[PDB]
Length: 210
Image (cartoon, rainbow, N blue to C red; front, side, top):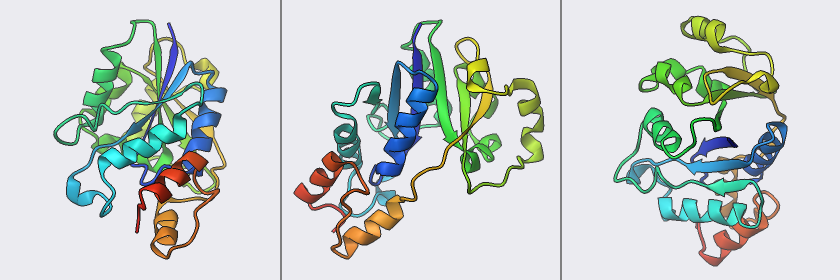
């Protein structure tokens, strides 16, 4: 089977921080493919004048011509937002039984896992890779103590089979944020080199974020 990664996010807009993490994750785990998964959200939660379709377009521009990096728009193609577990089952439904699926998530996001819809069923379809960075409190809530005891492994290389295990990885993400970028564009300042060139060209050509 193949080794497939899932990298979810709002990508408003997708930036250099996101893409560098994607590249590094794909290399560290020797992924055959790393899918960027733009998350769906209600229309009123979208940045004014920047639609879900445009967030998707920018991610497509960011991964165009880049091997191993693709985009999966399934969440956006639905009429409304989806629960992570549904997206996960939808993805696994198209894969071979022996394909290994790795879902990348941030530490803070991981610490709230117990709040996700049917959270205990996630590891049924994939391995969860938790990204820890300089900015994080290395102390998970009591609610996850057992899960970690039952499913965690020391390193990515120890992940075995289609899914079922949890591991942690270290990364020093570039100090770039979508909020920072939107602020700069709002002020008519250049975000060149803060986002992939193709994304920059798209933002300027469609005059996004004011």
